Image (cartoon, rainbow, N blue to C red; front, top):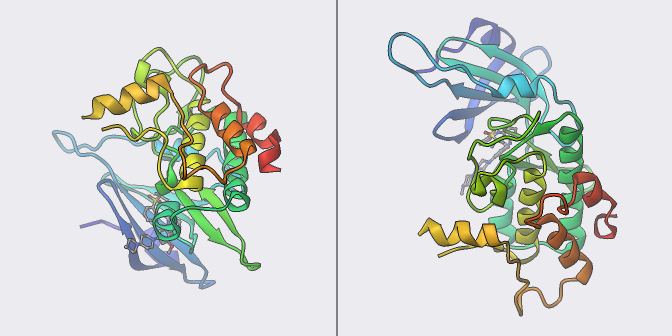
Length: 268
Ligand SMILES: COc1cc(N2CCC(N3CCN(C)CC3)CC2)ccc1Nc1ncc(Cl)c(Nc2ccccc2S(=O)(=O)C(C)C)n1
């Protein structure tokens, strides 16, 4: 039973539900004056004891970010029980569904998607922002007039600013960087690790660390042994394998920055 604020209903016509989850509801909505379509993300704040709700972080970060490979924030409205975000609607849906539908991608296609993602990451890191939740489900597929596709990064819910090492253990096990799991302190490059895992999935359809018991999974990540198994990876270029390898280094100082990803021949 969402209490939609007057200011939102005044300018937008709320539409159909396009997604639903444990913390947010996302709806299609239409701006009355222009008929332009947008997404309305409704974030349910956590209720505590007494008449109060927990404060949220997403908007503090979203307010700062403006980039073509990032879902644009149009407007925000905070009420005691939930938070309202009007955001650009990306009609092609998200990358999780695309991957299940398409299975795997060509190198020309995957590199273009990685080029997109690393651009977003380079930008965020230039602002000292770590996303900490980069994975296909948080990536949206923009479909161009020319038939081409581009990625847009959304959902800044776990995002924060890096000023010295961070320690909060968070994320999705498949995509989570070893230093996060090691609890020795982490920073911006956890996003590169995530991008590496995504690129790996794009070329073969399965993740590099699949585990067995969530114990085997975490050990695999900490050890970082990246394989490119036959026959799945036989027709994939050495250039692609080299780049993914550099993104998935346990040694944080050796692991590529986003700039280094964009400068690699495979993405150019
Ligand atoms: C209309 O465009 C979209 C369609 C879908 N899918 C959702 C799943 C659905 N399938 C149908 C078939 N089923 C077999 C599986 C489900 C198809 C349409 C997903 C996302 C979008 N576009 C979109 N644009 C901006 C935002 Cl802002 C957002 N946000 C957004 C939308 C949905 C969920 C979460 C977020 S999110 O904002 O929390 C973030 C993860 C991007 N979603």
